Length: 97
RNA sequence: UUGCUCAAGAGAAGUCAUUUAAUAAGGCCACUGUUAAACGUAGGUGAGUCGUGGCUUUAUGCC
Image 1 (tube, rainbow, N blue to C red):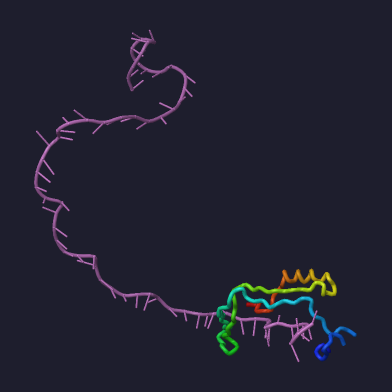
Image 2: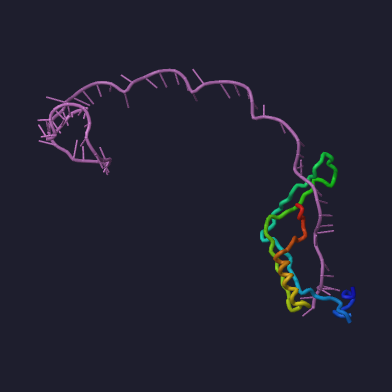
């Protein structure tokens, strides 16, 4: 909280910490063409909150990351991050569909 | 250390249930492959099984 109401980085315990890891956003390798999916839910009772449309994209995603390994408080923490980068569980999205 | 430092639009959802492209139709009616002749005379070959049996003089040939 104090990091936003002061100019320096200390206020003494540190006020903030720039993350040693920074990753750019992932972009699709292929230009997006308008593709949607129908979503009508089962049942004869056709009220609202049914017949929805979901946009999807059938391409590959690429992203760029960079870490200052020296900036890490514990130098050994870079290895678990690499393991996570290769074994990335799921990037937030409609994993159900 | 950058109007910065931190920052998931996220969790869930069947486009479903039903429908014969069906009923009818001749590619049909006509056509001669007609008419005539001297063979004068000189062109060749690719493929197994093994020790007496009925006649006949061993003979040597027949089945």
